[PDB]
Image 1 (cartoon, each protein chain N blue to C red):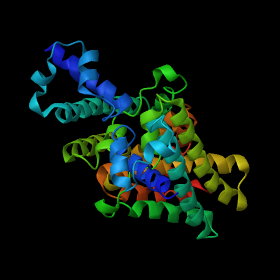
Image 2 (image 1 turned 135 degrees about the vertical axis):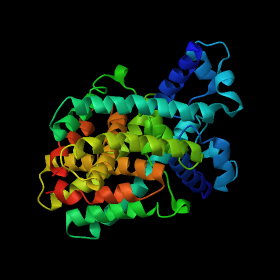
Image 3 (image 1 turned 30 degrees about the vertical axis):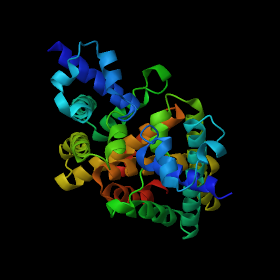
Length: 184
Length: 184
């Protein structure tokens, strides 16, 4: 079902870029390049069902991107600053701006639909866990490691929102310059 | 004379909680309690024109909150925490939850409408300026104060994002614990 993957990938791309409400089923069908396999693969549950898997899909890709930066350095603080710098590079070019992978959709559906909020909550944890695992590999206790995880994650999300609004990466670089003192 | 306020207040409230795309102009008239004054006061044009004023409106309210908060303590660090703690209490009860005042709409419209992105960029700057002023009055250099202003603003926006997705204030209280070592 290459057509299933096209629809899912297309949904993930559009949800991160445009948000949940701004993205319609018509637009997902139009950009996927599939012949009505939408309701076939995401039957009478439609948008919310498709969005749920889209979030998980987006979640895994990001989760993987974070681990990669964590693997690129033995110094936990350096590995974290590098991830933030790579994320910030997307803004020095309006063309390469991806939006807010999971955060935008999550903030839009938090008060409507527990299923989406649940999945977004589950995905954010997976991301901070990547940060938590790396710190734990450096002496931090599980509880302390988990806290820096949610703190670092929250900061990056905030930096992305501001960098996107400002169409400039300064916010994110600013956050990067703080990792050392917070992790201390 | 009284109807404009009802629309602006309802628009501001809805855009903040539901976002730009999910907020229809019919729901605004319906919930404002005002009679057909929407298109009257915002000479046609429509949603975007109303949205620009709604963001400015929401902008002033938050600006006043930050300002009132900076006045509650001579100590900048303590004043900043108090503001974060106040922002965080909106989550103790799902009923008192306000979305992301400006950030949600800014993340949704950033890549489209330069007018909307522009007003959001300016509003955020106004908030950052309040933090900066407090820091400057306390000895901090202009550059550092303004940078800490953007940093603080970015962290709070991210904290609200995570706190909303989790319907739990912890992410923000976690952010508050960091200001002592961030504003040295």
